[PDB]
Amino acid sequence: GRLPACVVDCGTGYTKLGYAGNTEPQFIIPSCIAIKESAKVGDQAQRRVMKGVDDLDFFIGDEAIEKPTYATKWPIRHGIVEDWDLMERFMEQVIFKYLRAEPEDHYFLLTEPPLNTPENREYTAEIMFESFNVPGLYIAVQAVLALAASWTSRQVGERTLTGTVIDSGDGVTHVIPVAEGYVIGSCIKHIPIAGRDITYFIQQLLRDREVGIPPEQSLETAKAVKERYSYVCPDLVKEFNKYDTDGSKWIKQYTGINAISKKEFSIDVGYERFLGPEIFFHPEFANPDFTQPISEVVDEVIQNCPIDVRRPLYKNIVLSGGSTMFRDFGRRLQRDLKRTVDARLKLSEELSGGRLKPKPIDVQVITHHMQRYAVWFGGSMLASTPEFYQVCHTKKDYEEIGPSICRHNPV
Amino acid sequence: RFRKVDVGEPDEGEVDSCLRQGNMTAALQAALKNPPINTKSQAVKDRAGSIVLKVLISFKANDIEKAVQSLDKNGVDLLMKYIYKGFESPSDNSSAVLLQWHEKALAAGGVGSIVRVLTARKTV
Amino acid sequence: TTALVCDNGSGLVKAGFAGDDAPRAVFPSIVGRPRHQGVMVGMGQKDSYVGDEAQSKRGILTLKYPIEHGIITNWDDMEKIWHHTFYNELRVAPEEHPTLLTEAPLNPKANREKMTQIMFETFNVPAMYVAIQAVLSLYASGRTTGIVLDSGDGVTHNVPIYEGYALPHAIMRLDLAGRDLTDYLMKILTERGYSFVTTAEREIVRDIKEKLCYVALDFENEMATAASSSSLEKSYELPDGQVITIGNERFRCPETLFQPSFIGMESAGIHETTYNSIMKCDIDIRKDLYANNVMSGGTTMYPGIADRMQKEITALAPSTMKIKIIAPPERKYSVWIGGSILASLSTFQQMWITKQEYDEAGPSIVHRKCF
Amino acid sequence: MDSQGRKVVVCDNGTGFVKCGYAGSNFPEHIFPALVGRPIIRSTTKVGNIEIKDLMVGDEASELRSMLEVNYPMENGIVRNWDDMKHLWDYTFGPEKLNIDTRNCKILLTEPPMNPTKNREKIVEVMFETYQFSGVYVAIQAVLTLYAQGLLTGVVVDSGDGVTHICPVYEGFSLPHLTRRLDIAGRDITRYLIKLLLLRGYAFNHSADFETVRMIKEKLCYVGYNIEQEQKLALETTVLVESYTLPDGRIIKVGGERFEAPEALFQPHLINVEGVGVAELLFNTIQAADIDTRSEFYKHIVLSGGSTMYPGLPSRLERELKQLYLERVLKGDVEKLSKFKIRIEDPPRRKHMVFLGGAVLADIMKDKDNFWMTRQEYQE
Amino acid sequence: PAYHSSLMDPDTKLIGNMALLPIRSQFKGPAPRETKDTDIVDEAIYYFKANVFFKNYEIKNEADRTLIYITLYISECLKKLQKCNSKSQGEKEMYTLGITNFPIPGEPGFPLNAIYAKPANKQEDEVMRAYLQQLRQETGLRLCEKVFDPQNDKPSKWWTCFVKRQFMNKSLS
Ligand SMILES: Nc1ncnc2c1ncn2[C@@H]1O[C@H](COP(=O)(O)OP(=O)(O)O)[C@@H](O)[C@H]1O
Ligand SMILES: Nc1ncnc2c1ncn2[C@@H]1O[C@H](COP(=O)(O)OP(=O)(O)O)[C@@H](O)[C@H]1O
Ligand SMILES: Nc1ncnc2c1ncn2[C@@H]1O[C@H](COP(=O)(O)OP(=O)(O)O)[C@@H](O)[C@H]1O
Ligand SMILES: [Mg+2]
Ligand SMILES: [Mg+2]
Ligand SMILES: [Mg+2]
């Protein structure tokens, strides 16, 4: 019968693949491509050049992460495609090898970050409509898909169309207020910190101390430490004191296998348990061009929104994306806002002179179970609806308007 | 709405006779006598241009020196105005020969001759 | 079937069934459109919202009023509000219910002609009528003589009526009403630093106005009192728990009913406009009008407006006679009540405009029947 | 100066720039930014032997900003920190600039229209209770630009740094019920320009960056005359892409942002200000005035303040006023529009027409009685 | 953010730009000695592990220029203690570092000439150098009890890994 639509979520760390209506993606793969090693060629003054059929000699995802004779390139950076040569090949194998979808028969839902420079929408439309010749396409916005994925799992009474989405992927973090199902896009703020930046901070902080980690797999070990030993602490200066005075509780041993030979190695895991996650609250640790804690950008985003929506946004802060599921993430952010917002009300109450003591604001931060793939799920639910097939840009539009059709996005 | 509205706004017998006599140098000079650059009509322009081309393609390629150097500088500039007209109507043969006439009128008139094609407010 | 009454107020639409004592629907006469293009799907469900949902959602919505100064200004949106009234608030198929509408006096004639056309050609009603709002106030007051001051969201007007006869040359109209008092309140609060501006936020100033404003019985004495004590200052909690404070602004706001010069009008105030209309009636009538001032419409709810009016007229009129201001508590709904009364009387049932008349007379019929 | 030898200073304390000189001058002495700053260490920027004082003000704070936290003492025409405004005034009358013995001077201030009440009270206070001036006045932005233009009738469109005001004046009579405030002004166009440069992949976040992007704005931005043809130009051809050099030497490319940012003045929704743009908001002011005054207001639109200096703003503002008039008054009689007389007074000196207006007024009234508020009349 | 000098009472003498806080210490030197246990050198030592990570630091008190100087000097002291192999051997070495000459405000080598204005009074120079030397003496001797792990007397893994992280990228040498 009628085939289900495809949903592809080309994240910076991971790409999620599948078909509409399924409860979860059929593949989650690392967003990388392995291309044949070629440095022995006389590349005396220029990049490598392709001949024959050799350009098809690549792998993607888990086939690409540890090949013995292929260079693993990572074509997505900050959420944006940085090299379309690699991305067009990556899409080629995603469609034909993994999904097994013939592209000329399935509508596609793609996704973008809200930072996505318009040229990238024009290019991605060209590739889907001209290379893969899709019948129809829709460049959905990741935040509204994340909120919908929460909404559709909510029990009665909690199920509501207003909430501050905080999406923190591998590449960048966005705070995006949605009220009444309309994204208040002019109020969006971007925090230039994500899982990549936390990983490299651990990677540095190990290399300063724990020399002994093989460089060929330094990144693997920093990533594995982050995913399993790390947590958001309450404050630094007490944590350093806690570690120094009771190190037998706080220091952990990590044991790794060297991929060359098979010898063991082991490391003490220490301050990089709570440093790392701290860079959300002190971005100056990992980025000198930013200084506001996340628990301040959130308040600034909300306090720009219209006064009638302002309370509903505090009541339904939705965390989404892989970097938000550090232990105690939400518990700290709430504790910061319910400090900042209370201080605001107290000041205005005092300036009223104790008349009309204002009703409080109950800051609440919610953290549903799908967060590793919530955006994809919200995509797969959307793509099963009949209305999806109306809002898609149909191929007959592109053949009249050209790539300019995809110039706009919801600001 | 509030920003929708547009607001604030040649002697053909003489040439034939010279060609049929074979007086090729005079046949060029006969075509260049009275250019309709003064004249509003279009048909008289395309007429005059076609008459000039009739001479240029019927000129022998070796004689283009004796042709072009015979003209005065005001004629050489007028020849350039007719040359850049020919290129607007390509054909199998015409562009191959107009490109040669161009390079000999260029030696006679120089790059300044081309500026007086670009800058003239009248079409020949 | 029983007739509907549908007072197309400039501010609140008040609707219900003829013979009932109070309207079964009251909702705001606003149409809202989303500020932000960025719908999702399923949610983000409509291009526009009407009535109470447009108040509730208002932070995302630009709100427009289809009625300004009592004249219909956006017919597509006004049709939307009528459609909302019958099919959503009352849940009535209008094709079989007579509907009594209302109008302010001295409107453009083309206004009511367009109005009656839509009723017969879009809602295809059997019958309808278009009564003057001031005349309806005497039905709700249960009397047949008196001068009605009705001052609504959009227009203030006086119609004097004696022994059941209107005096059409003494009718007076003044385009000050609850809208302009709100914009003035929205202005004067800038003296405190409380900016608002947004059309959504004007609805908050409107609520501030309703809950705190009052009319001083001696403006200059209260002004000099507010200079001395904090006693008049009352705080108000905005939806985000910012607590604003308001002092002499509480009564300067409705004072521009009596001193229109505050907002640059050249007109005399509402007291003198009333008095001038009495002095435009014959000598024998005046004795009765002074006894029977009937206040009507929303802005007459300001605390003290009855006392201030009574004080002011007794200073202009000859001192030898009683002046009394009739002001029941339900005077906000007077016009709807007076419609429900009129549509119930047996003697009225003969004077409905009917489809069979409109089909032969065309829209001009409303200028012939409804007088 | 005055006959008694008293210096008659004139002083605009804008949220952007102090503009402060002597009455009767044709130019302001001593333009400098209303800025205060304090030394900090950054791990990413070089430190040197340039002495940074424990507090810096004004011009020096703006040029040494690379090693300063910096603050604007006044916003939207309202004083935020009276302590920093005291420092800014202390610099204004100080040895750096107007080296005046304030106790002997007469000073002409200005105040924005419809401003908060207690703002003016505390300004007038400090002039008699800290600087001890011999006389004060608080002039109105609207009448001053009319003195600089020599007019008696017009509609001023004063577009400063913090906020934009439209103020009708007719034959010297004020029309204060027609004053209209538009919340967009040059500070928000700079916040908007940052948000657009972030979309080309640049980053600007520190307090020192806000002044750098202001200078990018002043150099490169312009108001598009016909926004459709500007968008067509940017899409069809590359010519708008113009380079700039940051103080760090990093080259940035600026493209269609040059006209997208100023455009907020005419399409306020682009920066989430709900309302109508300056052209329509002006037009709705004229159409509120008494019917026969309207034909004079159209002949005397007066622009003032630095946020009018965008190339093409008068030309664009003419076009929209003509389209509004054809649409709403002439109902489409496009032949009849040729009779519409409209003048936008665009003097190139208009960037300082408020101070120039005060220097005229104070020179006309240097020695009169009922004008200057004296310190003898104060404290009662 | 950062950690800022907490101990400045409503009055205490400021020399040049720098506050002459007490220092609970046995060495000679000008500063008061009595009723202290928490102290300006202990704040620097207690904050140091956090305070070096912040890339931006706002001077807002004369006592910050006191605390900053300690936090700078601790990054010179660790450079020695890292190479030692006993608490006794480090502690002996740290005396010689404490005596060692360091540049004063305004000298061509002093790191923060933009923020520390030079002295000029002869008694100001002597009091300042006597104070700074007293600061150095205690700051070293405090760390010698803390960097060397008592289980083996060797310089600790944890403290020594900060040697690459000079505070705010400013050397004191
Ligand atoms: N349990 C965890 N705790 C903290 N971080 C995690 C955890 N699991 C995964 N991550 C990190 O989240 C990053 C972002 O994941 P995801 O949001 O799926 O990527 P993308 O943003 O590309 O879709 C991953 O690259 C991984 O480094
Ligand atoms: N309690 C109140 N006090 C003062 N004014 C009120 C009060 N309630 C409503 N209003 C004003 O009444 C106006 C509505 O008048 P109303 O007669 O109900 O509408 P309409 O005139 O359109 O029929 C509103 O603009 C509101 O400002
Ligand atoms: N050449 C220019 N073009 C456009 N805008 C300018 C120019 N020069 C300055 N500006 C802007 O105008 C303001 C300069 O201050 P000013 O016009 O004196 O405002 P104010 O008087 O209200 O302080 C700043 O907001 C600045 O961004
Ligand atoms: Mg992602
Ligand atoms: Mg009414
Ligand atoms: Mg100004």
Image: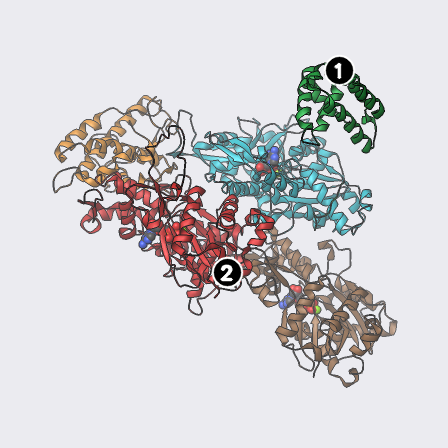
Chain colours: A red, B green, C brown, D cyan, E orange
Viewer-side residue, C198 vs E67: C198
Viewer-side residue, C229 vs E112: E112
Does the residue at mark 2 contact the one at mark 1 (Cβ under 8 Å)?
no
Left or right relative to A214: residue A380: right
Q: Position of residue D334 (x, y in %)?
A: 80, 47
Q: Position of residue D36 (x, y in %)?
A: 49, 35
Q: Position of residue C130 (x, y in %)?
A: 77, 73
Could you tell me which residue is drawn at 72 percent across and 42 percent down? D319
State which quadrant residue C185 falls in.
bottom right
Q: Which chain is disc 1 placed on?
A: B
Label 1 residue SS: helix
Left or right relative to D47: residue C328: right
Label 2 residue SS: loop
Viewer-side residue, A89 vs A388: A89
Specify the amino acid type for callout 2. Answer: Arg
- The numbered mark at residue A403 is none
Under 8 Å from ligand 3: the CB of mark 1? no
For this orientation, the residue located farthest to the bottom is C346
**What residue does disc 1 label?**
B73
Q: Which chain is disc 2 placed on?
A: A
Could you tell me which residue is drawn at 74 percent across and 23 percent down? B58
Specify the amino acid type for callout 1. Answer: Lys
In this rendering, is residue A324 above or below C166?
above
Residues packed near mark 1 inside 10 Å, few (<14), some (14 to 19) or many (20 plus): some
Could you tell me which residue is drawn at 53 percent across and 46 percent down? A122
- The numbered mark at residue A355 is 2
Q: Nearer the viewer, mark 2 or mark 1?
A: 1
- From mark 2 to mark 1, how far is it between C-alphas? 97 Å
State which quadrant residue D136 falls in.
top right
Q: Position of residue C58 (x, y in %)?
A: 57, 61
Viewer-side residue, B79 vs A359: B79
